[PDB]
Amino acid sequence: VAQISPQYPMFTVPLPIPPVKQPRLTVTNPVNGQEIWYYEVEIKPFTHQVYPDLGSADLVGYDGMSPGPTFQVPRGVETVVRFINNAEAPNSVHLHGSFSRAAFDGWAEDITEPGSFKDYYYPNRQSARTLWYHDHAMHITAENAYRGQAGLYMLTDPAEDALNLPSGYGEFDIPMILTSKQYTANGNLVTTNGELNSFWGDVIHVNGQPWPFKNVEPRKYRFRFLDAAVSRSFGLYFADTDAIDTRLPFKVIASDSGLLEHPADTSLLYISMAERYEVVFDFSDYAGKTIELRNLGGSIGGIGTDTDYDNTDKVMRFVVADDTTQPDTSVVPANLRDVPFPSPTTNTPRQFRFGRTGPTWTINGVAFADVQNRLLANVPVGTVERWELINAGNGWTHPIHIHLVDFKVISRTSGNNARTVMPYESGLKDVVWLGRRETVVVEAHYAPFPGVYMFHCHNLIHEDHDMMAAFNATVLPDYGYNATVFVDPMEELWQARPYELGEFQAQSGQFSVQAVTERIQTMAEYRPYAAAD
Ligand SMILES: *[C@@H]1O[C@H](CO)[C@@H](O[C@@H]2O[C@H](CO)[C@@H](O)[C@H](O)[C@H]2NC(C)=O)[C@H](O)[C@H]1NC(C)=O
Ligand SMILES: *[C@@H]1O[C@H](CO)[C@@H](O[C@@H]2O[C@H](CO)[C@@H](O)[C@H](O)[C@H]2NC(C)=O)[C@H](O)[C@H]1NC(C)=O
Ligand SMILES: [Cu+2]
Ligand SMILES: [Cu+2]
Ligand SMILES: [Cu+2]
Ligand SMILES: [Cu+2]
Image (cartoon, rainbow, N blue to C red; front, top):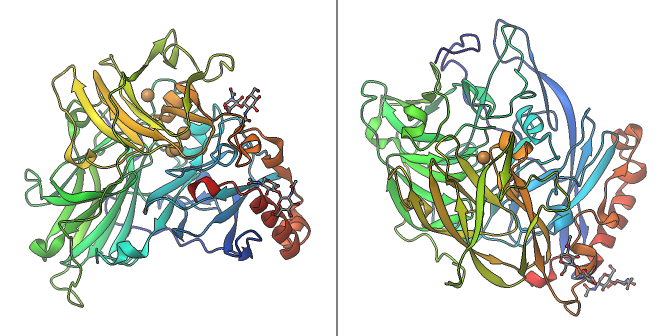
């Protein structure tokens, strides 16, 4: 299909790397004496010159950038992140991949208005993995994320550094955040407002930049792919520009929830919205060559229904030097980790159908706006349940996301006989792609925290109109652990608060060292994550 956005100078701008986000300070947790890292992020509009010869684009992002800055937090270190809304529409921050308490999880209605902020208390006790934080405000999640509110959150673990994977953020360990946008004739963004089917986009970006290039050395690199697009799913392959007909093999080492048990040799990677895979690619064998990262055509080989345009088959280019500066010491071990799978169950799976009810995208016929019916499941905390995710259509696909949990992919049947479970789906995941006429079964441990949580399709257009629902991970009233103040996402205790801009810029008032200290220490005393010990 003919490209609609104006022509871009392909592969002329180097791949940008989002800067590491540093904490402002640390507060000592009164309960155990340990340091909690405290950060401040300001949500605000900014201008970005995307087409060198046209006008600029109007974005809104964390700290005035897109992607937002990258967090790097070691397991065991609790963090508190104060997201300050200084924009012109409401926000709700969701750290995807983290078992946060309900009121810190970005519940769609748990909104912060302009002129307010909300403090998020993150546990960071889970396995090393690439998380990402992004907006979740009800009915406007698509435009908010699209205009720039998304960013990386790397949970790290020293035992994992002992594997000696390629390393160094921005050196040999490179984030690859894919988006897919559309631009107007004067180089501004085309809004998603009005789109009720899917917003495909015809200009592919990596890390905020359309069709970038990167100079690389002939050695191993670790790539952290994240499909951050509104609606576009990808089929990823590498190919020499001289032989685009031939796929260069590589290794997948991680999925949503962390490392696989063993590296999976792949030459084609399906990745859908909200999905994260880490890949090690070996440029050794291609010294002097240019490698193109490409995108499978025909709506991802017939798995999807995405529209393909003139240039959406291309992602970026890697120009490989003749030699390395220093010798590649890194390795990709055959054994990565023991994957902590849920204790298996064979209780009949709970069925969910993702489809259409009139003009609305629904889950078992309900829309999220329907407060009285959106709570589709009660699961006692500590329970393992299989869920059967069903897409009976050929006209839509749905990457399904379940909050709180990590899950194992049990099976996939395609009505088009297209595929089953992939080798890179061998580990633990929190989003799984239901392609054309696929039903997938997943197995998750609903643990270890009680609360009301979302689950939905991560096609943001579908999500907003209105393919989202809720589940309750329940406990008995004698459970304790302050469950009473942590189960309801709208719990007033944790709601947003107004601030004055002078206070924020002067780092005084609610933003003074002492006030931040007292507030965090008080949150801490509630001991929200103690059940994870
Ligand atoms: C989700 O489950 C929680 C925990 O089981 C429910 O909270 C209980 O609700 C009853 C009736 O209001 C109270 O007597 C209990 O004290 C509550 N328990 C706790 C731990 O607070 C909660 O109502 C459910 N949420 C929704 C929206 O249904
Ligand atoms: C549940 O929350 C309350 C309030 O955060 C905790 O009680 C506070 O504990 C601190 C220090 O441990 C005391 O100085 C306060 O006086 C307590 N406040 C109240 C209202 O009791 C309590 O320990 C938490 N309990 C659990 C089981 O996590
Ligand atoms: Cu998400
Ligand atoms: Cu999530
Ligand atoms: Cu969908
Ligand atoms: Cu969500």
